[PDB]
Amino acid sequence: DCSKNFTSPNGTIESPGFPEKYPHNLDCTFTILAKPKMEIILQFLIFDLEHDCKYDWLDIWDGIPHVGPLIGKYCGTKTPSELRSSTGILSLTFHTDMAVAKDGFSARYYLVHQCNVPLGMESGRIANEQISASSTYSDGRWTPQQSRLHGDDNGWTPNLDSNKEYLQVDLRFLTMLTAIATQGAISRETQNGYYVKSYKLEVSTNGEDWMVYRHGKNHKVFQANNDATEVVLNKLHAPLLTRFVRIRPQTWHSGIALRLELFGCRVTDAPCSNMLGMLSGLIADSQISASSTQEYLWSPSAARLVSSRSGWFPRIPQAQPGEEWLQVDLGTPKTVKGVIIQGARGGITAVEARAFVRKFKVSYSLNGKDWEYIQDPRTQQPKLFEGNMHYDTPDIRRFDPIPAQYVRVYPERWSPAGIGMRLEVLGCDWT
Ligand SMILES: [Ca+2]
């Protein structure tokens, strides 16, 4: 048996037989488990796999393998970037085929103890490998890794200065973003000052479905710099739950040069705000159910925040308000303090094709049989929660804490395509 679990405060994870070459025909699962308020830190020391990772690979998973999100798939000679997870579970599945073996890998994991924290551009906590761009200037002197705030060596500049370029950051885990700070840059070679004067923001949970950030009807244009040295910070009028962030310059002085910091926090930094297992897969399929489901090709995993490639859809998605529900059995009683609601993906090129919930109700139960709705203190009736404005970008909706083993989300309003929904529940231990 290849597979292993790791619970000790500090440890080693490695390819079978390391430092010998790795065996053929392997499929191993390495899982690190941590109790709450503990951060998992994973650092690679050696990495060397056969090289598109079509043959041999190491997949890293934000939870359970093939259930929770894929953080990345790695092969070849380039060691994975360091990972810091606050999910409570980090998994690795190492796959090898019938021929060709290399040295493999060796890694170490550690278990260690206002949403306004810098996310790591200036600290280096955002690794070089997490930063990329649509293009870069042809001399190699204005690279994406030169886009860190207060960097002493130029900045990021694209191949050609237009409004179709972007600096991209992969935060690896779903993270709250609350502000962006930018600078221009002064040429060490020439003394010319270059800066971006305005930008747009584009975000995704998965790298494939993107949302340009709006203020009202229209795309938000953030005003940026007025010199090549001073930091201009913009606070987002509405904070964002995201993984991938793109900064997309719209205007500049003399040319696009960019230095950047991102500000925010973890979902769990708020009290009683642990993700209870839909995203990760610690809530099993058997614990997920609905009033109705699409008649063919339904798996309960379709309902899972972020990891699902589609969504829950009732049997007739153009339903009756308050009749359809998605239920989560948390497995044991909990204190529940919110949900994260998301739209349905798959099929995006057509705006009217996008299925998402715009308004909803919540009920909860310890019985599984007797249900109470969450109340509006004003109208003395079931509270109508705001849903999503987009099919990928999720929205956290907190409420006054409640004791529950079961939670139901009842779609009330929804996009023209009908009800489509992915979900997570937020809370902590019952007390
Ligand atoms: Ca092989």
Image (cartoon, rainbow, N blue to C red):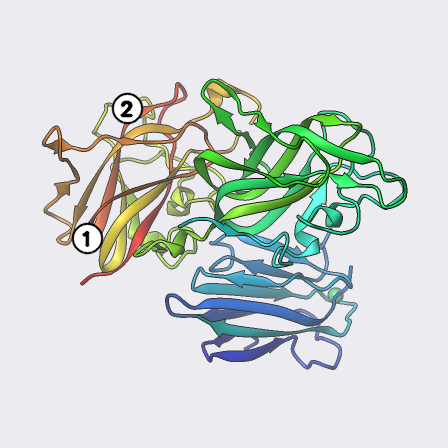
Q: Residues within 10 Å of mark 1 (few under 14, many from 20)?
A: many
Nearer-the-camera pick, 134 or 364: 134
Side of 312 relative to 257 (left or right) = left
Side of 229 relative to 326 (left or right) = right
Residue at image coords 43%, 56%: 280
Amino acid type at image mark 2: Ala
Amino acid type at image mark 1: Ala
Please tell me in which quarter of the rendered image ligand 1 is found.
bottom right
Q: Nearer the viewer, mark 1 or mark 2?
A: 1
Q: Which residue is mark 1?
A: 404
Circle 2: element type: loop
Q: Position of residue 203 (x, y in %)?
A: 55, 36
Residue at image coords 71%, 62%: 56
Q: CA distance from mark 1 to mark 2?
A: 27 Å
Q: Residues within 10 Å of mark 2 (few under 14, many from 20)?
A: some
Side of 275 relative to 108 (left or right) = left
Mark 2 residue's CB less than 8 Å from ligand 1: no
Q: Which residue is mark 2?
A: 319
Mark 1 residue's CB less than 8 Å from ligand 1: no
Q: Position of residue 284 (x, y in %)?
A: 36, 56
Residue at image coords 25%, 32%: 324
Side of 181 relative to 86 (left or right) = right
Q: Quarter holding the C terminus? A: bottom left
Q: Position of residue 210 (x, y in %)?
A: 56, 33
Is residue 369 visible to the viewer in this orientation of the structure?
A: yes
Is residue 27 visible to the viewer in this orientation of the structure?
A: no
Q: Position of residue 179 (x, y in %)?
A: 51, 41
Asked where in the image residue 157 lies, by quadrant, the reply is top right
Q: Quarter holding the N terminus? A: bottom right
